[PDB]
Amino acid sequence: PENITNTIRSGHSTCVRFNRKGDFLASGRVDGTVVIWDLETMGVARKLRGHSKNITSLSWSRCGRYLLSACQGWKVILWDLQDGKRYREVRFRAPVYGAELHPWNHHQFAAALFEDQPMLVDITEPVEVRYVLPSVPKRTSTETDPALREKQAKEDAKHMTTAIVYTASGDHLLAGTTKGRLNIIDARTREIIYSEKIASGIITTLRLTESGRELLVNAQDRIIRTFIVPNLSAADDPIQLPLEHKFQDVVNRLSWNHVAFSATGEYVAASTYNNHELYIWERGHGSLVRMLEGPKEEQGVIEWHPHRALLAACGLETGRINIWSVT
């Protein structure tokens, strides 16, 4: 028995994200508005209008006081929800795939940009300080014949970063690229310390579990993957990123639109390109536990509640948010 406990709509939702206590849900819309829903009454607590193009990501501060939103219109904004204020604002030269707040410091974020270099931005003050982040390790000055340098550089430049998250401590960034690589970046040196090809297309989503010990990866090769994250923040060298499970549908050759971990990391959910279903697998043994049909529409971004077995999803056609109670 499928159970949809709530359907809400304010504009066409393109993204959703629960805060960490789970009493509030943020929604971003096609028109750039961001909506804060009070989950007790399921009504709108406030509307934030700072963007004018599709919201692409939402990231909450540890404390729930601040919310970082990004859009296709090249902008990232840090909202103060204590007063609804635009607390910080950073404009790039390209659409933002997504921007993530440092897990312990709402004054630093990392962003991945469409056809542009990924960025680490310090927003402690008003007039940010930006730092370019690397997509590819640095080659030595002597390793390539001069006659080959132009073509090698052109090829290296096809490696572009499409998704990025902080590790739990904030000391490293995990980034995905157009060439299916997972890069581990030291956030203080901004140098790549490890890189491994884990997929055979563009990496579109990265997400960590709460402890930061497991990584979920969506990529364009029709396969969802979880990995065991290495011991990084420890004082002890470059490192393995062992695959845990692959989740896929071989006979229907389904592609996955968005993916999400449940509160404890027990379940992985995904929405399906060009289909209406949501799929839920369990990470204990990798098996498929549920296929949800819900309404008759293709689903986009999905997000689990941080404490309870609730799965929210944005419809691509209607922009409604449906919330399933998952048993």
Image (cartoon, helix red, strand yellow):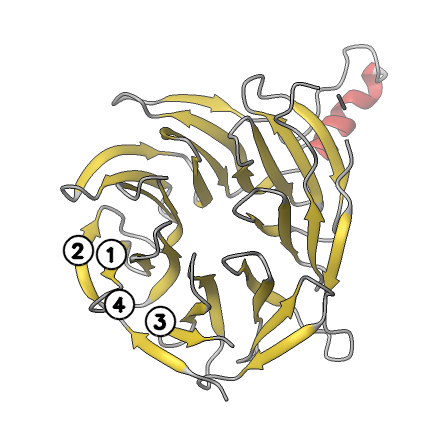
183 or 49: nearer the eye? 183
61 lies above or below 239: below
Other-residue count near label 1 (Cα within 10 Å), few / some / many at <14 / 14–19 / ≥20 = many
Q: What mark, if any, has residue 36 been given in the picture?
A: 1
Which residue is identified by label 4? 11
Q: Could you say whether the residue bearing mark 1 is in a helix, strand or loop?
A: strand
Q: Are marks 2 and 1 in contact (CB under 8 Å)?
A: yes
The CA span between labels 2 and 1 is: 5 Å
Q: Are marks 2 and 3 in contact (CB under 8 Å)?
A: no
Q: Earlier in the sequence, mark 1 or mark 4?
A: 4
Q: Position of residue 190 (x, y in %)?
A: 58, 21
Q: What mark, if any, has residue 46 been given in the picture?
A: 2
Q: Quadrant location of residue 255?
A: bottom right
Residue located 28% across and 54% down the image: 32
Specify whether residue 136 is in view. Answer: yes
Point out the frontmost of discs 2 and 3.
Answer: 2
Q: What mark, if any, has residue 319 been given in the picture?
A: 3
Q: Earlier in the sequence, mark 1 or mark 3?
A: 1
The CA span between labels 1 and 4 is: 13 Å
Residue located 51% across and 43% down the image: 114
